[PDB]
Image: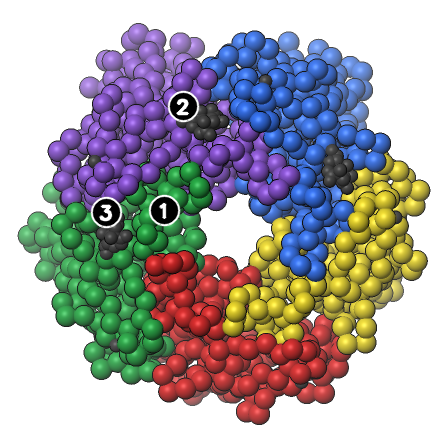
Chain colours: A blue, B purple, C green, D red, E yellow
Amino acid sequence: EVLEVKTGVDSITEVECFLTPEMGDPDEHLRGFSKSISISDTFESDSPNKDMLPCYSVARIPLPNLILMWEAVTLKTEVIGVTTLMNVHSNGQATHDNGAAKPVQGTSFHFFSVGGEALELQGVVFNYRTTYPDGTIFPKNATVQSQVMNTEHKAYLDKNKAYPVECWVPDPTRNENTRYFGTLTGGENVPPVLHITNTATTVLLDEFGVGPLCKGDNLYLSAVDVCGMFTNRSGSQQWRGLSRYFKVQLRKRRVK
Amino acid sequence: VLEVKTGVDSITEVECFLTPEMGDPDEHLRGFSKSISISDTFESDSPNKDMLPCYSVARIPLPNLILMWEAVTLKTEVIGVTTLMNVHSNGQATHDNGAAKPVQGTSFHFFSVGGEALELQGVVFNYRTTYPDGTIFPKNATVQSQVMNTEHKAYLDKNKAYPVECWVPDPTRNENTRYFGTLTGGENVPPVLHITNTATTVLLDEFGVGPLCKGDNLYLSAVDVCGMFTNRSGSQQWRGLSRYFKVQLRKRRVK
Amino acid sequence: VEVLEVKTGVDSITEVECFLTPEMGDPDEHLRGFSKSISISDTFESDSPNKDMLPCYSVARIPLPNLILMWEAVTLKTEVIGVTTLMNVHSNGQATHDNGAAKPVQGTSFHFFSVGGEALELQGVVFNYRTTYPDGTIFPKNATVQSQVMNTEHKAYLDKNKAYPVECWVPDPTRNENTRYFGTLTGGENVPPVLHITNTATTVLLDEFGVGPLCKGDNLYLSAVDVCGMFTNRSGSQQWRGLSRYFKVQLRKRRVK
Amino acid sequence: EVLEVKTDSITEVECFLTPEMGDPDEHLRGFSKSISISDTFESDSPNKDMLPCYSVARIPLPNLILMWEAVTLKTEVIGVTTLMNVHSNGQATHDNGAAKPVQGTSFHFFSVGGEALELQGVVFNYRTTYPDGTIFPKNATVQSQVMNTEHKAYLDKNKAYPVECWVPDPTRNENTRYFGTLTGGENVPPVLHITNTATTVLLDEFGVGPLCKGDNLYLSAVDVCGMFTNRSGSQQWRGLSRYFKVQLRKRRVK
Amino acid sequence: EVLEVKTGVDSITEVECFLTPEMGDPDEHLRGFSKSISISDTFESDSPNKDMLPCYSVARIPLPNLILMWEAVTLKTEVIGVTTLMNVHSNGQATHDNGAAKPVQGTSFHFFSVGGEALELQGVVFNYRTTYPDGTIFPKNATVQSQVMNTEHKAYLDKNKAYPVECWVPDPTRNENTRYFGTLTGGENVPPVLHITNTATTVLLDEFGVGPLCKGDNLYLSAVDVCGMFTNRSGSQQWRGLSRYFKVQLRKRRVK
Ligand SMILES: CC(=O)N[C@H]1[C@H]([C@H](O)[C@H](O)CO)O[C@@](O)(C(=O)O)C[C@@H]1O
Ligand SMILES: CC(=O)N[C@H]1[C@H]([C@H](O)[C@H](O)CO)O[C@@](O)(C(=O)O)C[C@@H]1O
Ligand SMILES: CC(=O)N[C@H]1[C@H]([C@H](O)[C@H](O)CO)O[C@@](O)(C(=O)O)C[C@@H]1O
Ligand SMILES: [K+]
Ligand SMILES: [K+]
Ligand SMILES: [K+]
Ligand SMILES: [K+]
Ligand SMILES: [K+]
Ligand SMILES: [K+]
């Protein structure tokens, strides 16, 4: 039972943080990148290394200790460091003779969510015979049905650097206490289009004027910002990701 | 069509997912078509069944009820969009040492909510195409069938039977259904798939009346051909994904 | 026409529902919806396209119930019919690469429709004034080099089906007071078709003063072009492909003085 | 001081402006000369018939203190479907294919004002020598490649001001409304919408449209649709005419 | 605390100017261009020449001396010289035999801000081993974490032609007293799309009806307009920038 909002000086707070991307980090110099992508020799033998798999990011933010619950009302969010994609002068492959290096481009996924509990995930796999690596949490006992929808694959985004992007999505049958937004833009040559502004606000209230209600006084933020692939001189490609800023305004809400 | 009932018991909701029906050429390839082959002449076009994506449909029974369930709102979403980030599974490298070419090219994204079966009109790219045993296709195709032959009328009344390429929603009918679709062509067309649990489509017409569910049945239909997967060899297969539906319904009295 | 009040009553409304088939050239008895394959002249002076190679405007004059009262067109629902046919990539087209599917229909499109109370009015404009348009078409007569940009002599009525080639006529913006027209040319040879369908969208046909097209002689004029792109054969030869268009129009009786 | 609107009180301007693309010979109205490339910045010296220019018409209004105030505009590019001629000495896209359609860099621009469009000069390359019979930035310096405030002009002559070295001056033009889109890239496809159902309101944030000094309305346009490539591969700009219809009303001023 | 707006003919003022782009200016004939872009063999050896790095533009505009503050309320802005990109006859590379020159295209960054103090910057680098050149102001003591987010890299955009675009962005964790807008459009061949009009106004008021308040009676304007790359006959590529016009309206506001 959701009752009234509490007012007065004491009754609002705000959360401000950033989530780093988790692209795989194949060595000590390559934070924000994946390992270069290799292609299996057969469909059955698909078997990606952990460092080659971008994962969902998540942070659990503790809120001032409070029945009253913190209610998330608005979000401002922004991808951090968009201009880094203008470095086309290192380690790259020329577009044509004497040209600059091919920039980061191709498949992107940009995703973020704000909830009063962990994001709920449904497992779907491109190829059910893919062997996901040790160190990742992935759909277990995958069958051919898992290539389209196997309802056995439920999980919570409850751990950072763990849930690979390619085999999990937000579960649309759950997540009543979360708001989520994502865009997959495919193709090998698609250009990144990245907007920044400190003037845009998303309102998190549902159809009844109620935002996510924070259980245990924790706010859950989740994100993926795979911007595309970087291409080395050899032609090998590595995913590149960026950090995401969150600012969330919250108010106290009485419940029963 | 009279008034809406109110009160605790007067609303219900349907929540489900429709699986895609892309052809399923073997026991490992659910969600995929058979690789596509090209006829040697225009006249000799003869696609195999496993190579033809078909419309999906589910009839959802509603609480037994003159009142009729009226579909009012819809939330819908393509499920498993991130699978298209698998570019390491024996695809064809974009260039020497590159990652695999992702799923791309021609897509059809379509969904409908009705109080009866979606009504279909048959149109063919090529009237001499021999559609295969086990599909339901425009019968007695003439050259006029390439643009409009009003004989080709059907109901989307069976799963994995109606090929996407030779049927569309009949604009001359479907008064009790709401449909939406986008065909995006070209072989290099990039998929653009959005997800969110914050978007609702209102199903009410210009008089504030939604689809009215005959016999207490809700009809959901879909196609989500996302593009084609290219194998190492160059062969291509349609790839489809599931669609989530959530529909809100209220009891409406009628005479 | 001084326009006066709308008439009411069960008797006072009617609707028109039909489809216009595309007129792409139809080069033989198996190729309804296609043009002849396209060939290119070696000079501007030798441009002489065959009729079967030229897409034309579609038109239908629809008789309305006989009636001073006039039928006033108020709303339109319209839809391109058969959009999913473009998923046929297995019918002797040209493989995009070794072992791949056939290149789908793509490239230059023109999607156009109008609703009016009289024939659509046309202005002739030509890419190349020395193009000789063929017998059996209606085209800009006495073309001069000024016809490549604007020659006010080239006025016509879309008063005949499969006759007015798309490429040399457009709706005349200096006229057409009693018609509503809408069109998009999307160029480029690799341009992907984007075709939306739905039965929930309505276009209101009333002007800034709340008046829609008034049907002279109790006729409603519907016009369309839906050139979807080009189909590429295995040989590399290319043919325009078109699709039919559905129209549903609501009309009401309007008194005029 | 702008005062009340009069309520005889309205008039309408209807016309078209032809494109001015270069017109290299008597058969190529609407096209430019084929484009050639200087081998150095210093040697850039385009011929006039290779340079699209701004189009302008000064339209005299009924003699009238009252001024004509421009309130609404309807506008359209004329002949959009000519771009479907892919059978006329173009270059096949591939063996046995149709000709490459017009595509690549486009500039679509129109303005309505109560005086000549005010122009600022900016040049890609300050060492470009602009030809006789054109009006161009004079005394160009390297600063002219980004902003040289010396280059002020009025769009006061047709077939004269090259598109490439002039833009509307955003520091002036209070008495004009202008709108333009430059869509670059060599392969970019043209997207041309036509309809007779769209109106643009010309009033500013205070409810005042352009006021016609000396009872003249100034219409300006550029519609470079792209480049046509012929069978040899050479490329030439292709432009189209623009329709304007403008509603005006009489306004008293002090 | 923000109190009432002043009224009267004397209560408003306006600022009108342009910011020139700062692309590198490799010689006396190439204002508005960078130096040719080259590609270092490794991240380790990445060492961009100063003339090769586009920088942020900034101007500090003094306002009429004024407790009252000037409050920025509206902005009109425009890229100046968009039609220059139609010069495809000047020292370029023909797209195909006998064709015109390939126009300016590829990665673009269009950005502008209006504030009552210097734009606040956060350093993010594509590659932490990039050696930024003498004469630039850049993230100091970069580590591998600087490739995603390192909170030590805080700066003010307080100097023209000094802060490279590629290693700095607006700090979303600050800039309360500034409004900023930017778009990074990536890709090797992405076409420029440039709109111009004198009929569009951006409102600078925040959600409480308050615009940027000008400390010390100074308005801060910042911009980047990297339009793409110019490809010369050899195929070497240079960034090309254009100037940006600003018109800002301000009003007097009382504060305590
Ligand atoms: C940015 C970078 O470090 N590139 C290097 C990559 C990556 O380190 C690995 O691909 C990580 O998986 O390795 C190479 O052998 C290669 O693939 O060509 C050399 C190249 O310079
Ligand atoms: C995803 C998958 O199964 N791919 C395999 C395909 C398909 O099974 C068939 O094409 C179905 O028609 O078959 C191959 O022989 C091929 O065409 O190259 C091997 C390839 O790895
Ligand atoms: C759809 C179709 O019929 N395609 C066929 C075309 C057309 O009939 C003509 O081009 C009409 O002009 O004719 C061919 O000889 C060709 O050009 O390659 C064979 C091709 O399969
Ligand atoms: K495996
Ligand atoms: K057959
Ligand atoms: K001829
Ligand atoms: K010169
Ligand atoms: K000014
Ligand atoms: K270094």
Q: Ligand 7 is located in which of the four quadrants?
A: bottom right
Disc on the earlier residue, 3 or 1: 1
Camera-side residue of D223 and D131: D131
User: Which residue is labeled 3 in the image?
Assistant: C244
The picture places residue A43, in percent across and down from the top left corner, at 53, 24
Query: Which chain contains the residue that carries disc 3?
Result: C
Give the amino acid at mark 3.
Ser
Residue at the top extreme of this rendering: B64
Q: Can residue A78 be seen in this view?
A: no
User: Which residue is labeled 2 in the image?
Assistant: B20
Is the Cβ of the residue at disc 3 closer than 8 Å to that at disc 1? Answer: no
Is the Cβ of the residue at disc 2 closer than 8 Å to that at disc 1? Answer: no
Badge number at residue C94: 1
Give the amino acid at mark 1.
Gln
Query: Which chain contains the residue that carries disc 2?
Result: B
Q: Residues within 10 Å of mark 1 (few under 14, many from 20)?
A: many
Q: In this view, does E217 lie above or below B235?
A: below
Q: Is residue B98 above or below residue E249?
A: above
Left or right of A63 in this view: A197:
left
The picture places residue A139, in percent across and down from the top left corner, at 59, 14
Give the amino acid at mark 2.
Pro
